[PDB]
Image (cartoon, coloured by chain):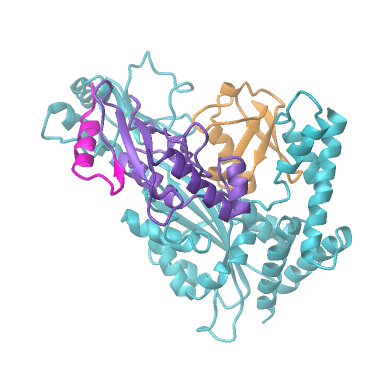
Chain colours: A cyan, B purple, C orange
Amino acid sequence: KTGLHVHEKIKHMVKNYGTMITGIPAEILGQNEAEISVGYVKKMGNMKENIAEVVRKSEMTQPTNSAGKASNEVCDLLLGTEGASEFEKSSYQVLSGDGSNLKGSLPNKNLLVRVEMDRFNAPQKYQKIKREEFNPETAEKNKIYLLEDQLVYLDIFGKVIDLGQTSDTCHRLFNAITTPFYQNYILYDEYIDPEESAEEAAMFEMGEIVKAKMKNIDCWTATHSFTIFVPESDSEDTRTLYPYQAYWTSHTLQQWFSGDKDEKLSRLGIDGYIEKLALLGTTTDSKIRSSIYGELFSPPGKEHVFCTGMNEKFSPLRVKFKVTEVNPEIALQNLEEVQEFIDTNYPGENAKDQCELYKIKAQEAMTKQLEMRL
Amino acid sequence: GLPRRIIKETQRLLAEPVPGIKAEPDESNARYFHVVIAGPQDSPFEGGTFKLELFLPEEYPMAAPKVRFMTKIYHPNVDKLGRICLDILKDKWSPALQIRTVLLSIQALLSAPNPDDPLANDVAEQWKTNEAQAIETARAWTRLYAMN
Amino acid sequence: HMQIFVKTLTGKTITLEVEPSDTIENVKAKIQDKEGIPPDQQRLIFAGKQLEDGRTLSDYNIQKESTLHLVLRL
């Protein structure tokens, strides 16, 4: 019931204060937003009344919708800067097929899980090229390159990675592809038939060569980040978890807590959540992946359109987790320090007027900076 | 020099077009689809028919297809030019997506606007502000530019 | 080779070591290593213009002691 007080406390504070739980003075936000947003001011005319509109347009006091920043703020509040920094040093563990290692990493103590989810950023394009033509720095990145004597992959960093093909195979595939359009095309075209022509057989064979070689090339890049608070419970059949998350260009942690999606996903139960999380990484069906992604990571209400049509999850996903312990008194003390900071520097009879006063202070600092500079 | 993907996409789209979406190519440039989307039911755009152009780049399907609303429409996601602000067309385009998915997303966005992280100007601020008269000004735009 | 700085609205300044050859996605991976933020969410602004994922640092005329801005909203 004390870890439950921790959860209730952080939920209430995020819901009522948005970005103010970061403990950062409004003046700093205003000044740095003025420093980044001076090029957007109209350079002519009465610009004081013209910087008024750029200050009004600003959303500097709105909480971040970067999921990584939200996870960082949650870790800060729950572990202090020190325990957060030490949690940073821990290594992620890839989730198992059944998610059993995660549930085995959840003893009946106040726990914090941090999850990083990766896309498989495999190359989707190929191009014939001659070794004289090839310059890795300027060439297109994350792209397969077919040469007369070599088949390489130019990765996301610009490192040429050989695909273990002989000059005979490469010469055959290079000369078999004659059509001028297929000189710079895609790797896995559904409408290509290998038995129709020799060129399309070449393209299919190259596609499968790359598809097999990528199976052991680290194409994983991070696409999502969230946290999970699992408090201690009286039993084991009443214990529950609460996922905390923002989503890039979708919603803030504030909006997540407002729609109570933490409680909705807590109703799934520990095993109920972990099973879906593991299936997300193990499945091959694109729409099963899409529906689980939308159930778990969408803002409340948009579960059924989050990953449909164009946002369909076609890339294989992988879930990684790290777990540490939460001392409820440290978390409550951090939250109390944030609350006293807010009440002392931004007074008011309710959190809402305090948020507005914070916004006004930020806007005034931004105005003073933009004025003293122009 | 049209890839068989383009012509077989066209053949499967004529063999199966979207209800309410009529896409058929013209001959001076076969990469051009005179697409027409009528306003879905229960929408402020219902009863109107919005003509759009869909241009396949030569880099299709590596590059996303250009789609532009010819008709003017009051919506918090298309601008004055009619450039639809699906994030498909600039970044998050992949060859797994096709013309039919682009048209599907355009129709769905017509049935469900998004004015909170949008591209439109006073349209978007007035949509998040006052949904009622925003919907109704969209209704009037429909009755003016989309009925004939 | 080269030191660059990345500042954010929160006031935090982080220091990366890169080369002009380094792709933007490599800088995003370094920011991930130092701050745990997924690259798919980082916006990098130099001289008021987004840095695009296919390009490199030398494409944006980014040289030594330069300062970039990590935008984490939309």
**Front in this rendered view, residue A289 or B86:** B86
Q: Which residues are magenta?
A: B1-22
Query: Where A289 sits versus B35, above or below?
Result: below
Would you say A266 lies left or right of A61 here?
left
- Residue at 39% across / 18% down in the picture? A134
Picture quarter with the C terminus of chain A: top right
Would you say B76 lies left or right of C16 here?
left
Q: Can residue B67 be seen at all in this image of the molecule?
A: yes
Picture coordinates of residue A220, whole percent (x, y): 45, 45
Q: Is residue A360 magenta?
A: no
- Residue at 82% across / 50% down in the picture? A360
Q: Can residue A222 be seen at all in this image of the molecule?
A: no
- Residue at 45% across / 30% down in the picture? A159
Picture quarter with the N terminus of chain A: bottom right
Query: Where A271 sits versus B54, above or below?
Result: below
Q: Is residue B16 magenta?
A: yes
Picture coordinates of residue A144, whole percent (x, y): 35, 30
Picture coordinates of residue A236, whole percent (x, y): 52, 83
Picture coordinates of residue A64, whole percent (x, y): 65, 51
